[PDB]
Image: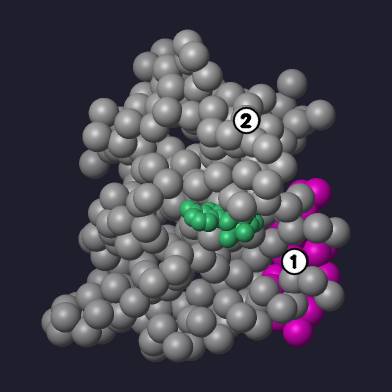
Amino acid sequence: EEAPVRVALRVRPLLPKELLHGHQSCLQVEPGLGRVTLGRDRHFGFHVVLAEDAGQEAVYQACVQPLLEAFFEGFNATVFAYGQTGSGKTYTMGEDEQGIVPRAMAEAFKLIDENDLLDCLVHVSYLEVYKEEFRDLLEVGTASRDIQLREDERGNVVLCGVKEVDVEGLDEVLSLLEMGNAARHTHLSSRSHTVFTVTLEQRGQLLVSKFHFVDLAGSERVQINSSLLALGNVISALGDPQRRGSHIPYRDSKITRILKDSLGGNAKTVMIACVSPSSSDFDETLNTLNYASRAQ
Ligand SMILES: Nc1ncnc2c1ncn2[C@@H]1O[C@H](COP(=O)(O)OP(=O)(O)O)[C@@H](O)[C@H]1O
Ligand SMILES: [Mg+2]
Protein backbone atom coordinates (compact mmCIF):
# COMPACT_ATOMS: atom_id res chain seq x y z
CA GLU A 1 0.00 0.00 0.00
CA GLU A 2 3.12 2.23 -0.08
CA ALA A 3 4.93 3.76 -3.08
CA PRO A 4 7.95 5.92 -3.99
CA VAL A 5 7.72 9.30 -5.72
CA ARG A 6 8.39 8.65 -9.40
CA VAL A 7 10.64 11.12 -11.20
CA ALA A 8 10.38 11.88 -14.91
CA LEU A 9 12.68 14.22 -16.80
CA ARG A 10 11.21 15.99 -19.83
CA VAL A 11 13.65 17.71 -22.13
CA ARG A 12 12.06 20.20 -24.52
CA PRO A 13 13.43 21.17 -27.96
CA LEU A 14 15.78 24.10 -28.35
CA LEU A 15 13.41 26.98 -29.22
CA PRO A 16 13.83 29.04 -32.43
CA LYS A 17 14.73 32.11 -30.33
CA GLU A 18 17.51 30.16 -28.55
CA LEU A 19 18.89 28.95 -31.86
CA LEU A 20 18.82 32.48 -33.32
CA HIS A 21 20.72 33.73 -30.28
CA GLY A 22 23.48 31.20 -31.02
CA HIS A 23 22.77 28.61 -28.32
CA GLN A 24 23.18 24.90 -28.83
CA SER A 25 22.11 21.77 -26.99
CA CYS A 26 24.16 20.87 -23.90
CA LEU A 27 22.20 17.66 -23.24
CA GLN A 28 22.59 14.17 -24.67
CA VAL A 29 19.28 12.44 -23.98
CA GLU A 30 18.94 8.63 -23.98
CA PRO A 31 15.25 7.87 -23.29
CA GLY A 32 15.50 4.13 -23.70
CA LEU A 33 18.34 4.05 -21.14
CA GLY A 34 16.45 6.28 -18.73
CA ARG A 35 19.32 8.73 -18.66
CA VAL A 36 20.82 12.02 -19.79
CA THR A 37 24.35 13.44 -19.96
CA LEU A 38 24.95 17.17 -19.29
CA GLY A 39 28.06 18.67 -20.87
CA ARG A 40 30.93 16.25 -21.25
CA ASP A 41 30.98 14.40 -17.90
CA ARG A 42 27.71 14.66 -15.91
CA HIS A 43 25.43 11.60 -16.07
CA PHE A 44 21.95 11.41 -14.53
CA GLY A 45 19.38 8.58 -14.53
CA PHE A 46 15.66 8.94 -13.84
CA HIS A 47 12.65 6.63 -13.67
CA VAL A 48 11.41 8.07 -16.97
CA VAL A 49 13.35 10.21 -19.45
CA LEU A 50 11.38 11.91 -22.24
CA ALA A 51 13.29 13.52 -25.11
CA GLU A 52 12.32 16.48 -27.30
CA ASP A 53 10.36 14.29 -29.66
CA ALA A 54 8.07 12.83 -27.02
CA GLY A 55 4.66 14.32 -27.71
CA GLN A 56 1.98 15.20 -25.18
CA GLU A 57 0.16 11.88 -25.45
CA ALA A 58 3.44 10.01 -24.80
CA VAL A 59 4.14 12.12 -21.69
CA TYR A 60 0.62 11.47 -20.40
CA GLN A 61 0.91 7.71 -20.99
CA ALA A 62 4.35 7.39 -19.42
CA CYS A 63 3.86 9.65 -16.35
CA VAL A 64 0.15 10.18 -15.64
CA GLN A 65 -2.21 7.51 -16.86
CA PRO A 66 -1.03 5.07 -14.11
CA LEU A 67 -1.97 7.71 -11.45
CA LEU A 68 -5.52 7.97 -12.80
CA GLU A 69 -5.93 4.28 -12.13
CA ALA A 70 -4.83 4.62 -8.49
CA PHE A 71 -7.12 7.65 -8.07
CA PHE A 72 -10.14 5.54 -9.08
CA GLU A 73 -9.09 2.89 -6.57
CA GLY A 74 -9.38 5.54 -3.85
CA PHE A 75 -5.68 6.56 -3.62
CA ASN A 76 -4.68 10.24 -3.63
CA ALA A 77 -2.41 11.28 -6.53
CA THR A 78 -0.27 14.30 -7.38
CA VAL A 79 1.55 15.20 -10.58
CA PHE A 80 3.76 18.28 -10.36
CA ALA A 81 5.82 20.10 -12.99
CA TYR A 82 9.15 21.52 -11.71
CA GLY A 83 11.89 23.54 -13.40
CA GLN A 84 13.16 26.96 -14.47
CA THR A 85 10.91 29.50 -16.13
CA GLY A 86 10.76 28.65 -19.85
CA SER A 87 11.50 24.95 -19.41
CA GLY A 88 7.99 23.78 -20.33
CA LYS A 89 6.09 23.29 -17.06
CA THR A 90 2.84 24.97 -18.22
CA TYR A 91 3.00 23.43 -21.67
CA THR A 92 3.36 20.04 -20.02
CA MET A 93 0.69 20.41 -17.34
CA GLY A 94 -1.78 21.83 -19.87
CA GLU A 95 -4.08 23.70 -17.49
CA ASP A 96 -2.89 17.19 -30.06
CA GLU A 97 -0.86 19.84 -28.23
CA GLN A 98 -3.11 19.67 -25.16
CA GLY A 99 -1.31 18.82 -21.92
CA ILE A 100 -1.89 16.53 -18.96
CA VAL A 101 -4.99 18.05 -17.35
CA PRO A 102 -7.38 17.70 -20.30
CA ARG A 103 -6.11 14.22 -21.10
CA ALA A 104 -6.51 13.00 -17.55
CA MET A 105 -9.99 14.54 -17.25
CA ALA A 106 -11.17 13.12 -20.55
CA GLU A 107 -10.11 9.65 -19.36
CA ALA A 108 -11.64 10.16 -15.91
CA PHE A 109 -15.07 10.87 -17.35
CA LYS A 110 -14.86 7.80 -19.58
CA LEU A 111 -13.94 5.68 -16.55
CA ILE A 112 -16.94 7.05 -14.64
CA ASP A 113 -19.18 6.00 -17.53
CA GLU A 114 -17.57 2.55 -17.57
CA ASN A 115 -18.03 1.81 -13.90
CA ASP A 116 -21.74 1.60 -13.85
CA LEU A 117 -22.06 0.03 -10.44
CA LEU A 118 -20.73 3.19 -8.79
CA ASP A 119 -22.46 6.48 -8.18
CA CYS A 120 -19.73 9.10 -8.68
CA LEU A 121 -19.46 12.83 -8.10
CA VAL A 122 -16.53 14.93 -9.35
CA HIS A 123 -15.73 18.43 -8.18
CA VAL A 124 -12.76 20.69 -8.77
CA SER A 125 -10.90 23.58 -7.11
CA TYR A 126 -8.25 25.81 -8.63
CA LEU A 127 -5.86 27.71 -6.36
CA GLU A 128 -2.83 29.97 -6.71
CA VAL A 129 -0.20 30.10 -3.98
CA TYR A 130 1.98 33.22 -3.94
CA LYS A 131 4.14 34.22 -0.95
CA GLU A 132 2.32 31.67 1.19
CA GLU A 133 -1.10 33.21 0.45
CA PHE A 134 -3.95 31.53 -1.46
CA ARG A 135 -6.09 33.00 -4.19
CA ASP A 136 -9.13 31.07 -5.33
CA LEU A 137 -9.12 31.26 -9.12
CA LEU A 138 -12.75 30.04 -9.42
CA GLU A 139 -14.28 32.57 -7.05
CA VAL A 140 -15.53 36.05 -7.98
CA GLY A 141 -13.12 36.69 -5.21
CA THR A 142 -12.06 35.57 -1.75
CA ALA A 143 -9.74 37.21 0.84
CA SER A 144 -6.54 35.19 1.38
CA ARG A 145 -7.13 35.38 5.14
CA ASP A 146 -10.48 33.60 4.57
CA ILE A 147 -8.87 30.55 2.99
CA GLN A 148 -7.36 28.14 5.51
CA LEU A 149 -5.61 24.84 5.29
CA ARG A 150 -6.38 22.26 8.00
CA GLU A 151 -5.97 18.51 8.66
CA ASP A 152 -8.51 16.10 10.15
CA GLU A 153 -8.10 13.31 12.72
CA ARG A 154 -7.48 10.78 9.95
CA GLY A 155 -4.70 12.84 8.32
CA ASN A 156 -6.84 14.11 5.43
CA VAL A 157 -6.17 17.65 4.23
CA VAL A 158 -9.24 19.86 4.65
CA LEU A 159 -9.62 23.14 2.80
CA CYS A 160 -11.73 25.84 4.29
CA GLY A 161 -13.14 28.70 2.23
CA VAL A 162 -12.26 27.32 -1.20
CA LYS A 163 -14.83 27.01 -3.98
CA GLU A 164 -15.57 23.45 -5.20
CA VAL A 165 -17.37 23.19 -8.54
CA ASP A 166 -19.17 20.01 -9.56
CA VAL A 167 -18.22 18.93 -13.14
CA GLU A 168 -19.89 16.35 -15.40
CA GLY A 169 -17.61 16.52 -18.43
CA LEU A 170 -14.47 17.78 -20.06
CA ASP A 171 -16.20 20.81 -21.58
CA GLU A 172 -17.12 22.06 -18.11
CA VAL A 173 -13.57 21.47 -16.85
CA LEU A 174 -12.11 23.42 -19.81
CA SER A 175 -14.47 26.33 -19.17
CA LEU A 176 -13.43 26.55 -15.52
CA LEU A 177 -9.74 26.40 -16.42
CA GLU A 178 -10.26 29.19 -18.97
CA MET A 179 -12.08 31.28 -16.38
CA GLY A 180 -9.52 30.71 -13.62
CA ASN A 181 -6.59 31.45 -15.89
CA ALA A 182 -8.20 34.71 -16.96
CA ALA A 183 -8.87 35.60 -13.31
CA ARG A 184 -5.25 34.97 -12.33
CA HIS A 185 -4.00 38.10 -14.13
CA THR A 186 -6.36 40.71 -12.70
CA HIS A 187 2.74 39.58 -9.90
CA LEU A 188 4.07 37.37 -12.73
CA SER A 189 2.90 33.66 -12.79
CA SER A 190 6.46 32.37 -13.15
CA ARG A 191 6.64 33.38 -9.44
CA SER A 192 3.57 31.55 -8.12
CA HIS A 193 2.30 27.97 -7.94
CA THR A 194 -1.05 26.70 -9.07
CA VAL A 195 -2.93 23.66 -7.83
CA PHE A 196 -5.87 22.21 -9.72
CA THR A 197 -7.49 19.58 -7.49
CA VAL A 198 -9.97 17.01 -8.68
CA THR A 199 -11.98 15.23 -6.00
CA LEU A 200 -13.75 11.98 -6.85
CA GLU A 201 -16.46 10.72 -4.49
CA GLN A 202 -17.63 7.17 -5.23
CA ARG A 203 -20.43 5.24 -3.61
CA GLY A 204 -21.68 1.72 -4.23
CA GLN A 205 -19.83 3.62 2.10
CA LEU A 206 -18.31 6.74 0.51
CA LEU A 207 -14.82 6.59 -1.01
CA VAL A 208 -13.16 9.97 -1.56
CA SER A 209 -9.87 10.58 -3.35
CA LYS A 210 -7.94 13.57 -4.67
CA PHE A 211 -5.83 14.17 -7.79
CA HIS A 212 -3.69 17.33 -7.69
CA PHE A 213 -2.15 18.82 -10.86
CA VAL A 214 0.53 21.28 -9.84
CA ASP A 215 2.30 23.82 -12.02
CA LEU A 216 5.06 25.11 -9.79
CA ALA A 217 6.80 28.48 -9.62
CA GLY A 218 10.06 28.79 -11.54
CA SER A 219 13.04 27.11 -9.88
CA GLU A 220 15.70 29.63 -10.96
CA ARG A 221 17.91 30.96 -8.12
CA VAL A 222 19.98 34.12 -7.63
CA GLN A 223 17.83 26.84 5.27
CA ILE A 224 14.36 26.08 3.86
CA ASN A 225 13.37 29.68 3.10
CA SER A 226 11.41 29.00 -0.09
CA SER A 227 8.46 26.79 -0.93
CA LEU A 228 10.46 24.94 -3.58
CA LEU A 229 13.17 24.10 -1.03
CA ALA A 230 10.46 22.94 1.39
CA LEU A 231 9.09 20.63 -1.33
CA GLY A 232 12.64 19.48 -2.01
CA ASN A 233 13.17 18.70 1.64
CA VAL A 234 9.95 16.65 1.70
CA ILE A 235 10.67 14.62 -1.40
CA SER A 236 14.31 14.06 -0.34
CA ALA A 237 13.07 12.76 2.98
CA LEU A 238 10.61 10.41 1.27
CA GLY A 239 13.42 9.06 -0.93
CA ASP A 240 16.00 8.52 1.81
CA PRO A 241 15.89 5.11 3.61
CA GLN A 242 17.20 6.79 6.78
CA ARG A 243 14.66 9.66 6.77
CA ARG A 244 11.57 8.10 5.21
CA GLY A 245 10.38 6.18 8.29
CA SER A 246 10.40 9.33 10.41
CA HIS A 247 8.14 12.38 10.35
CA ILE A 248 8.05 13.94 6.86
CA PRO A 249 8.55 17.73 7.12
CA TYR A 250 5.33 18.95 5.43
CA ARG A 251 4.60 21.88 7.77
CA ASP A 252 7.16 24.29 6.32
CA SER A 253 5.10 25.56 3.34
CA LYS A 254 1.48 25.75 2.19
CA ILE A 255 2.46 23.86 -0.97
CA THR A 256 3.62 20.86 1.03
CA ARG A 257 0.77 21.16 3.54
CA ILE A 258 -1.93 21.17 0.88
CA LEU A 259 -0.32 18.04 -0.63
CA LYS A 260 0.46 16.29 2.68
CA ASP A 261 -2.02 13.40 2.16
CA SER A 262 -1.09 13.31 -1.53
CA LEU A 263 2.66 13.17 -1.57
CA GLY A 264 4.56 9.93 -1.19
CA GLY A 265 3.55 7.62 1.64
CA ASN A 266 0.26 5.89 0.73
CA ALA A 267 -0.42 8.25 -2.20
CA LYS A 268 0.95 8.13 -5.72
CA THR A 269 3.14 10.98 -6.88
CA VAL A 270 5.02 11.89 -10.06
CA MET A 271 7.37 14.81 -10.45
CA ILE A 272 7.99 15.88 -14.03
CA ALA A 273 11.23 17.81 -14.02
CA CYS A 274 11.30 20.03 -17.11
CA VAL A 275 14.58 21.23 -18.58
CA SER A 276 15.79 23.45 -21.36
CA PRO A 277 18.54 21.88 -23.50
CA SER A 278 20.00 25.32 -24.19
CA SER A 279 23.66 25.91 -23.35
CA SER A 280 22.53 29.33 -22.05
CA ASP A 281 20.56 27.41 -19.41
CA PHE A 282 23.38 25.07 -18.35
CA ASP A 283 23.57 26.15 -14.67
CA GLU A 284 19.81 26.08 -14.04
CA THR A 285 19.51 22.76 -15.86
CA LEU A 286 22.19 21.33 -13.57
CA ASN A 287 20.23 22.70 -10.60
CA THR A 288 17.12 20.92 -11.84
CA LEU A 289 18.88 17.64 -12.51
CA ASN A 290 20.36 17.72 -9.00
CA TYR A 291 17.00 18.56 -7.39
CA ALA A 292 15.21 15.79 -9.21
CA SER A 293 18.00 13.33 -8.29
CA ARG A 294 17.47 14.05 -4.58
CA ALA A 295 13.96 12.66 -4.90
CA GLN A 296 15.11 9.20 -6.04
N1 LIG B 1 8.01 19.86 -25.24
C1 LIG B 1 7.90 21.04 -25.89
N2 LIG B 1 7.83 21.08 -27.24
C2 LIG B 1 7.73 22.25 -27.89
N3 LIG B 1 7.66 23.46 -27.31
C3 LIG B 1 7.69 23.56 -25.97
C4 LIG B 1 7.82 22.33 -25.16
N4 LIG B 1 7.82 22.73 -23.87
C5 LIG B 1 7.74 24.08 -23.85
N5 LIG B 1 7.66 24.57 -25.11
C6 LIG B 1 7.56 25.99 -25.44
O1 LIG B 1 8.52 26.66 -24.64
C7 LIG B 1 8.03 27.89 -24.11
C8 LIG B 1 8.09 27.89 -22.58
O2 LIG B 1 7.15 26.89 -22.19
P1 LIG B 1 6.29 27.13 -20.83
O3 LIG B 1 5.33 25.97 -20.87
O4 LIG B 1 5.77 28.55 -20.79
O5 LIG B 1 7.36 27.08 -19.68
P2 LIG B 1 7.31 27.36 -18.13
O6 LIG B 1 5.82 27.26 -17.78
O7 LIG B 1 8.18 26.32 -17.47
O8 LIG B 1 7.85 28.75 -17.90
C9 LIG B 1 6.61 28.01 -24.60
O9 LIG B 1 6.62 28.89 -25.75
C10 LIG B 1 6.23 26.61 -25.03
O10 LIG B 1 5.26 26.54 -26.07
MG1 LIG C 1 4.46 28.47 -16.88
Quadrant where the C terminus sits is: top left
Nearest the camera: 82 or 206? 82
**Snapshot quadrant of residue 103:** bottom left
**Residue at screen point 61% across, 52% down:** 16
Locate residue 203, reporting x and y percent. 26, 77
Q: Which residue is mark 1?
A: 135
Mark 2 CB near ligand 1 (8 Å cut): no
Horizontally, residue 21 falls left or right of residue 211, namely right
N-term-proximal mark, 1 vs 2? 1
Q: Residues within 10 Å of mark 2 (few under 14, many from 20)?
A: some
The verdict on residue 135 being magenta is: yes
Residue 279: image tag? 2
Q: Is residue 97 visible?
A: yes
Q: Secondary structure at mark 1?
A: strand
* Magenta region: 129-150
Q: Is residue 260 above or below residue 163?
A: above
Quadrant where the N terminus sits is: top left
Locate residue 100, reporting x and y percent. 42, 63
Locate residue 7, reporting x and y percent. 40, 36
Nearest the camera: 77 or 283? 283
Q: Is residue 86 above or below residue 213?
A: above
Q: Is residue 291 above or below residue 175?
A: above
Residue 15: image tag? none
Amino acid on which the number 1 mark rests in the picture: Arg
Q: Secondary structure at mark 2?
A: helix
Q: Is residue 175 above or below residue 280?
A: below
Nearest the camera: 14 or 228? 14
Locate residue 264, reporting x and y percent. 40, 39
